[PDB]
Amino acid sequence: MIHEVDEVLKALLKGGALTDSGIDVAFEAPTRDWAARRNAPVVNAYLYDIREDVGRRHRGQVAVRDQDDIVVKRRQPPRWFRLSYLVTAWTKTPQDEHRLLSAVLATLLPREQLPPYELPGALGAMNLPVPMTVAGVSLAEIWSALGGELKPSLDLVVTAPFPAYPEYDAGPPVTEGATVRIGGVEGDPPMSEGRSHRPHQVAAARAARK
Amino acid sequence: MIHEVDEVLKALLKGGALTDSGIDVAFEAPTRDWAARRNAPVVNAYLYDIREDVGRRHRGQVAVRDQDDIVVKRRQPPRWFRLSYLVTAWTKTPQDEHRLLSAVLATLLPREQLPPYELPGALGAMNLPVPMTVAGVSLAEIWSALGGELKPSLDLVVTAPFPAYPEYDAGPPVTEGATVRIGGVEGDPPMSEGRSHRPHQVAAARAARK
Amino acid sequence: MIHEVDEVLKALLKGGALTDSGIDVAFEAPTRDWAARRNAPVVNAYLYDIREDVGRRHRGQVAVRDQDDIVVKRRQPPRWFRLSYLVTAWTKTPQDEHRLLSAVLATLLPREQLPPYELPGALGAMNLPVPMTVAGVSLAEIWSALGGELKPSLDLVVTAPFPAYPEYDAGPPVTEGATVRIGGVEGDPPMSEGRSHRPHQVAAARAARK
Amino acid sequence: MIHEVDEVLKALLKGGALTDSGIDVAFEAPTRDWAARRNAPVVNAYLYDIREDVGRRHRGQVAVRDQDDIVVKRRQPPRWFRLSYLVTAWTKTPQDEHRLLSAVLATLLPREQLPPYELPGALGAMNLPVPMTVAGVSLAEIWSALGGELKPSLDLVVTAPFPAYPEYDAGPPVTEGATVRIGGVEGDPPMSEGRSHRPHQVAAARAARK
Amino acid sequence: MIHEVDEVLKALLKGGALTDSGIDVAFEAPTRDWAARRNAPVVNAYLYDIREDVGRRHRGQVAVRDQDDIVVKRRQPPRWFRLSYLVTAWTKTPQDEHRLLSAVLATLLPREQLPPYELPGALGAMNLPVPMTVAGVSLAEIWSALGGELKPSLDLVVTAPFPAYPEYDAGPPVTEGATVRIGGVEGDPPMSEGRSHRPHQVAAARAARK
Amino acid sequence: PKPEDVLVAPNFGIQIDGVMVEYLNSVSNLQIEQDVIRYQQNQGTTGRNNVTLMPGVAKDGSVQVERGMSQSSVFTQWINDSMAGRMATARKNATIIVMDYEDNPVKRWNLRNAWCSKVVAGTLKAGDTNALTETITIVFEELVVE
Amino acid sequence: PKPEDVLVAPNFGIQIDGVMVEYLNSVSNLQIEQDVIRYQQNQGTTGRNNVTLMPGVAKDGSVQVERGMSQSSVFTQWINDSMAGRMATARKNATIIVMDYEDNPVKRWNLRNAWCSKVVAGTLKAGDTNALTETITIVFEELVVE
Amino acid sequence: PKPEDVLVAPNFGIQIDGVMVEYLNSVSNLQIEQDVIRYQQNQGTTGRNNVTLMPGVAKDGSVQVERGMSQSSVFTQWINDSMAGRMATARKNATIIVMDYEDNPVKRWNLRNAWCSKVVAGTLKAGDTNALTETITIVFEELVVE
Amino acid sequence: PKPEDVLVAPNFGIQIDGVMVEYLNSVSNLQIEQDVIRYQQNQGTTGRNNVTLMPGVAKDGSVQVERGMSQSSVFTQWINDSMAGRMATARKNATIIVMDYEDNPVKRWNLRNAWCSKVVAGTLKAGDTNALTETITIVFEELVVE
Amino acid sequence: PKPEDVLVAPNFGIQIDGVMVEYLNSVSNLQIEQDVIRYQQNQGTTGRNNVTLMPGVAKDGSVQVERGMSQSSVFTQWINDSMAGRMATARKNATIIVMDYEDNPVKRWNLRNAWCSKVVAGTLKAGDTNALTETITIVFEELVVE
Amino acid sequence: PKPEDVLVAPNFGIQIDGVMVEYLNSVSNLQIEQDVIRYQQNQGTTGRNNVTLMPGVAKDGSVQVERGMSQSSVFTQWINDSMAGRMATARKNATIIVMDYEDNPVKRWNLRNAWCSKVVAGTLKAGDTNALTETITIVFEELVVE
C-alpha cells in the first residue's frame, strides 16, 4: 500500500495551501544528475526506507462475523509499517526554496493522522487512521548514499496498516446445544448418553443473543 | 517562517557590529564550486536541517475569545521547530577570516532571544519570543555530505514557533442559563420540567464577569 | 543450505501475488553497472551477510535411535544462521516501483515461518521450521559499500538451521544386566562376584519398554 | 578574540624552544594542495571548530562600580568558548618531523593557563586566565574532512573568554535614605507621611562604607 | 605462527568436504583489481586484523622442570591472539557462489577447536588447543577500506597462543637442607650455628617425592 | 468503526475548575487501583488447601501534571490557598481528557476533590538549553474513569 | 516431528470469559511456583548434619496483559464490577494460548477465579511518537498449565 | 502578551543579604511542599467507605548551590559564622530570581532564615579538564514564591 | 598434557534421571559454598586479640536451567509431580557435565535430591524476534563436584 | 583581579607531617558539614505553626587519597603505626592545597588529628592496561578551611 | 631510582602452600582494615565539644581469586578438605606477589590461616564465546603486607 500513500501525499501537496502556483511533486531520487536537469520549482518526496512499527504490533485471533451475528473467519490484527519520505523543495533562488519549504511544512503540519475518508479505496478499505508525522527527529550519511548534496529536508513518516491474511475458517455453529456424558472414572458404571440442552434453553439463548 | 528567520539573520548581521565594511551575507551552499567563484569577504549562513523541538511541545485546547469576553475558537499551542544554520566567514587571508568570525561571534552573542516587535509581520504575528543559540554544542560528516571542506563554523540554532492551529469552533454562548429536570430513576414519578435559572441570578452572573 | 533458501525465495516470489506478470528474480549485486543494463521490471534479492543466531543455540548430547528403540548415535542440536537479503524492485517508473515493492511486501507478509513439507531435500531433511522475517528491523553504509545508490529495500532475514554433526557413536547395549561386586574397603574380606540380574528381571525390563 | 588567540599561539611557538631555526607557523588548511607546495619545515596550526564551554558558564547580575564605590552597571559573566587547533609539523624527513613535533609539544606543555600580562589588548582587557590544553583527548574522519592525509597531530584547546555583557544601567543612588508609610490595611486610620532616616543615620551609613 | 594458521586453514579447506573439485584457496586481498583477474572458482581467506584475547590472559610464574623432578625454569603462560579472516567464495554464477559458501560453512562448522597433533610443528609444540569460530560477530566499513565491494562473507576467528619468554633461571636445588640460627633480638646471647637437618630427615624427604 | 479498531494518539488535555490551565507538557500515570486480600485456609475435614483473593477498598492517588514555567502563577495561587487551610475553595474537581483524531474526546478521567500538594521548579543551569519545567503533584480522593 | 524439535514463536493469544478482548501487545511472565521449606537436623548418635528441604503450598500470582488504548472499555467495566463487590460475576476463567507456526494451540495456561486488580494508563507526553498503552494487572487464585 | 504565552529561559540569579555572591553555575530543585494526611472511615448506618485527604504544615527544605570555586570564601565565612553559634548574623534572607529575555524579574522565591549547612569541594583529579566546583547546601525555614 | 594446561570451552550438557531433557540454552551459577563462623577473643593474661574463622555446614542451593520452550512438557510434569506431594518420584539425581574439545567429560557436578521448584515463561511480546525461553529453578540438598 | 574573577584549575597537592608523600592521582570530596536540628512548635494562644531549624556540632569525617602503586610503603608504615596503638605518633596534621595558574597556594584545608584507617589495593587483572591504584582513607578529627 | 619513582605494572602471581596454583586471571581487592571508634564529649567546665577517633581491632577479610576452568581440581580438593572439618591441613599460608618490570617481587601480601570457603562456576551459555571462569573466595584471619 505504498502506491496509495504516495498518491495521498501528492494530492495533499497539490491540494494543500500551495495553490498559488502549479508546482510539480516528483518521487525521483534527488541525485546530482536529477538536480542538474530540472528547470522548474519542484517538490521531491523521495522514499527512503521501509520499517515495521514493532511497537504497535498486536497478536490475537480477531473474529470476523457475517450478517447472522455468528463468527465465520479468524484473522490477525494488521501490522503497521513505517514509510519514510525525504521531502525537499527545489527552486533557483535560495530564499524561494526556503519559502517553498515553509509552505510545505505549513500544509503538512495540521494533519497529525489521516481519516479513512480521504484515503483511496485500497487503503480506505481498512477504515483505520493513517498517522503522518513531519520532522520529529544521520541525514548526512543518507544524503551521501543517494549521491546528492546535503540540503534542508523534511522526514515524513507514514504508518501504513498492512494486512496479515491467514484467514482461518471456524467450524459450523452449534445449533443443537451441548451434550454431556457422565460416568465412573474407572468404568464401574457404564457411560450414559446424558441427553443434551432442552429446546427451551436453546430458544432462550437464541432470543437473548439479540 | 524559514525566510522570515533568514531576513532576521541578514538584518542582524548587516546591521550588527560589522558596520566597518559592506560585507555580504549569502545563504548559498558553501561547496567547492561556490567557494571557487567568490572574490569578496562574505558570510555564509547555509541552512543545514530542520528538526522539531519535542521538548517544548504543549498539547491542549487553548481558548480564543473576541471583544465580548466570550470564547469563540479552540486552537492548539504552536509547535517549535529548530532550524540550524552553518555560519562561516570567507576571506582571502586566514587571519582576516578569524577576525570576521570573531566579529560575527561578538554580534551574535548578546541576542539570546528575539523580541516580537523586531520580527517581520509573519513571525511577529505570534507575539512569542524566538530563542537563538550560538555554538551551543559530527561537523566533518556534515561538511563531507555538503560537498565542501572542513572550516571553523557556527551552529546557529533558531527556534521558530509554527502554529498548529486547527481553528475548531465552539458552540453558541448560553444566555438562558441551565435547566435541571429531576425525577425517579425507574420512572415511577414522571420527569418534571424543573424550571431554570432566575433572571436575577443570570444578571448577577453576567455582572460578575467584569 | 544457502542454495536452498535462494530456491525457496525464488519459488515464493514467483508463486506468490506476482502472478499477473512474469517478473524476473535476480540475486546479482545491485551495483550501478548492474542497474545500468537491466531493461525489464525485476526483483533483486541480493545476499548481504551471514551471521549465526547465538540466542537460539542449544548444546547437549541428543540421542539418536534405530528401529529397535535403542540409541545408537549421539549428536548435537543444529545451529541456526541468520541470512540477510536486500530485496529491491526495479522498473522504469517510481510509482510502478512502489507498486512492485507493495506486492512483494504483501506476498512475503503472511509467511512467518516455513513448514518443511515444501522445502528442498537438504532443507526438508531437517523437518524443522525456518523462520522468515520481512522488515523486523545503517542501510546507507551497506549501499555505499555495495557500490549502488540508496533505494527502498526489504531486509529479509531467514534462519537456516545449519547442522553440527559430531556423530559420537554409542557403546553396545547392555543385555546381560548389571553385576555388582561388594567387599571391604581395606580388603579384609575378599571381593565377591556378587552375581547379576536374574533372567526374570531382565525379561520384565525388556517388556516394560513397550 | 580569535585573532588574539592565534597571535598568542604564533608568538609562543616562535618564542618557545623553536629558537635554533626560524620555522614558519601557518594557519592554512593542511590539504593535499597546501602540502604539495611547501618546501620548508613549517608548523601548521589550523583552526578546526568553535564550541561553547557550557560547564564553565556562570549566570548572574555582576555589579560594576565607578571610583565612588557605587555600582552603576549590571553585566553578565563572560562566556567561555573552546577553540580547537590541529597542530602538525611538516619537514622533508619523517625523523625530522618527529623531532619538530617533540619540540612543539615540549614548548606547549607548561602553558596550563595563560596569564593576562602578555596577551594583546582585547584579551588583556579581560584580566582573566586563558586555559590551554595540548593533548587532553575521530581524527581520521576529521582529517578526511579537509581531504588531507592522516598525520600525527596535536589538539590544542584554548578557552577564550568572550564577552556577553548586556551593560544594563542601574538606578540613581539613594541619598535621602528610605521613608516608610504606615497605617490601616482597610484604611480605617488616615495615612501618615512616616518621616525618613535622620541625618545622623545617613552620615553614619556613609561613614561606615570606608 | 600466523603462517601455521594459514597452512592449517588451507589444508582444512582443500581436504575438507570440498573434494568434488580442485578449488583454490588464496590469501590475497579481494580488491576490485584482484577480483577482475580471477577466472576460476576460488576461496579467499584474507586475514584482516590481529588482536589480543585479553579475556584469556593468565599471569604467573609457571615452573618448568627436567627429568630429575626439580624445577629449573620459570616461564609465563602464553598470550592468546585473535586472528580474523574474511572468507569469501568467488564463482561466475551467484547460485554457485552460494553453494560454495554453504560447502565452506559445512566443512568449517564441526571444528570448534583443533587438536595439537593436527597443527604443524611450530604451533604443535605448545600442545594447546586452538579455538576456531566460524560463527562470527561493521563489515561494510571493512570492505570499503579493503577496496572491494561488499559480498556475503564469513568472519573466521582463530585463537593462536603466542608464548612469552621471560625465562628466569631458578637457583640450584637445596641438597643440604635448611639451617636455622637462633639467639637474642638485642644480641645479649650470641647467635649460634643452630645445626641443620639430620641426614635421615633429608633422606626421608627425598624418598617422599616419589 | 469498532471501538477496539480506533487507536488513541497522545493528544490530551486537562480541565480544572477554578484553575486556568490550558496546556500541559506531560501527565504522569493515573491508575485505577484496588486492594487484593489473600487469605489461606485448609479445607477442614480433608486438608486440601484453598487460598482466596477478594476485593478490598478502592484507592486514591496523585496525578501530577507538568507545565512549562511562565509568568502565570495559577498553581502557585492554588497551593497558597491550600497552605492557608481554605479548603472550601482549594478542593476542586478535575478532568483529564484524551482524544483520538478529529479532536473528539475518547476517554475522560474525573478527579473528585483534587487538590494540589507539591510544586517543584526544574533545576536551573547556566548552560541549560531546555526550557524550565514546573512539576505539580495533584492528589485526589477518588478517580472515576468515563 | 519430536515435541522438543519444534520450537515456539511468540504467536500468542488470550481468551477471557465475559471480557471481549482479542489482541494484546505483551504479556508479563507467567510463573508456576511452589513454596520450599528447608529443615536442618543432626543425627542423634553420629552427629552428622542432614538438611531436608521439601514441598509447600502452590502459589497464586498476577499475570499482566498490556494493550493499545482505544474506545473500548472492557477492562474498565471489569474493574468497575470488581470494585463494587459483585465478585459473583467479576471472577472469570482466563486462558493464555501459545501457538505454533500453523497457529495450532501448543501450550495453554488456565487462570482460575481471575479478576482484574489494577488498571494503569500509559504516561501522556506531548510529542511522543508512540501509541498510548494500557496495563492491566489481573490476579488469580490458581494457574494450571495444560 | 498573555502570562502563559511568554516562556521562561534558564536565565537566573541569586541575592543573599550579607553574602557577596553574584553568579552561580546551577541551582537544585526548589519545592513548595505540604504534608497530606489520609483518613479512612466507614459510614455508621450504611457502611460505605469514605477516605478523606486533608492538609498538614508547610515543610522546610534545602537547596544546593554549586559555583565555580575561586579565591573568594564568602560561603566559608558563612559556614564559619554558623558553626560558632553566632546565629543572629548567620540567618539571612535569600532571594532566587528567574528573569525573562529582557532581563526583567519574573519569579522571586524568598527564603526566610537561611543559613549554610554544608560546603563540599568537588573531587580533585590529576587529569581533570573542567573547572573544579563547590557545592553549598542551604536550609531555609520558609520558601515563599512571589 | 597437564591438567591445568587444557582449557575448558562452554560445551556442556545435563542429565536428569527420569526427566527427558537433552539440551539447554543456559545454566546459572553452580556454587559450592560453606558457612564461616568468626569468633573474636582476647588473651586472658596479655590482652592480645585473636580472631578465629572456622567451618560451618555445607549449603544447598538452586540452579535455574533455561531452554527453548517447545511442545515438550517434561518440566511441567516434574513440577506437577512435586506439587501434589508425590516426593518419592519427584526427587531425582541430576548431573551437569562440562566436556573437553572432543566432547570428553572433564567436570561433573552431581546433584542429590533435586526437584524443580519454579517454572517461568518468557515475556510474550508481539514484536519479539528471538524465540521464547523457559526458566526452571531446581533446588538441591547436596551438590558434589566429581 | 577580583577574588571571584580568577578561577581555580585542578592543580593540587598534599602535605602530611611525617609521611613522605609528594603526588596523588586524585582526592575525594572534602566536606565541611554541620548538624541541623529541626523543631516544630505551635503558638500557645493563636495556634500558628513555627518550625525552628538550628545549629549542631561540627561534623568530621575522612577524605580519601589515591596514588600510583610503587615500591614506597609510607602508607603501609602509617597504618602499621596506627594498628599497634602507637597513636602518639600515628595522629598527624595534614594539609590539602589548591593552587592557581602561577602555582601559588590559593586554598588550604588543614586536617587535625588525621590517621590512616583503610588501605585498599587496586584490582589486579591479567590484561589490564591501566596502572595499579592504591586507595587510602585518612580519617581526621577536624577539618579547618583556610 | 627512588622508590616512589618506579611504578607497578599489573604483573602479579600467587603462591599457596599445599595448593598447586601457578597463574590467575584476576584477583579482587586486598584491603588492610582497622576499626575506628568515634566518641563525643563535652568539656565539664567550659562546655566545648570534643570528638575523638581512636583505633579498633584489626579486621580479617576475604580475597576472591579467579582462574580459567580446566581439568585440575586443586580448589575442589581444598574446599573438600575444609568441608569435612580437617582444618589441620585446610588452613594454609598464602602469598600474593606484585613484581616490577624486571620480574622482581616488589610487594608481598601474606595471608595467615587462609582456607577456601566458596567455589563458583561461571555461567554456561551455548552461544558463549569467552572461556569458563572459576571464582574462589579465600578468607584470611590476618593479612600482613610486606
Image: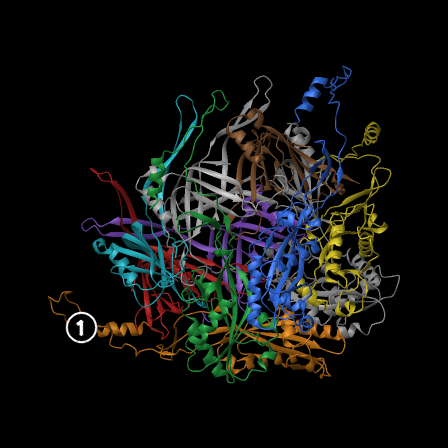
Chain colours: A yellow, B blue, D green, E orange, F brown, I purple, J cyan, K red
Residue that extends furthest to the left in the rendered view of this protein: E188
Q: Is residue E29 left or right of residue J14?
A: right
Task: Report whether residue I37 is seen.
Answer: yes
- Residue tagged 1: E195
Residue F100: percent from left, percent from top: 73, 41
Residue D177 appears left or right of F119: left
Position of I67 relative to B102 (above/below): above
Along the line of sight, the residue nearer the viewer: A161 or F139: F139
Expressed as whole percent of the image width and height from the top left, the position of residue F118 reads 53, 36
Question: Relative to the observer, which residue lies in front, D137 or B84?
Answer: B84
Q: Is residue A87 visible?
A: no
Amino acid, disc 1: Arg
Q: Is residue D157 left or right of residue E194?
A: right
- Residue placed farthest to the top in the image? B189
Asked which quadrant contains residue J81, the reply is: bottom left
- Residue E129, horizontal then vertical, whole percent: 52, 73
Q: Is residue A76 above or below residue J136?
A: above
Q: Quadrant of residue A37?
A: bottom right
Task: Tell me the SS state at disc 1.
Answer: loop
Q: How many dots with numbers?
A: 1
Q: How many neighbours does mark 1 have within 10 angstroms: few (below 14), some (14-19), or many (20 or more)? A: few
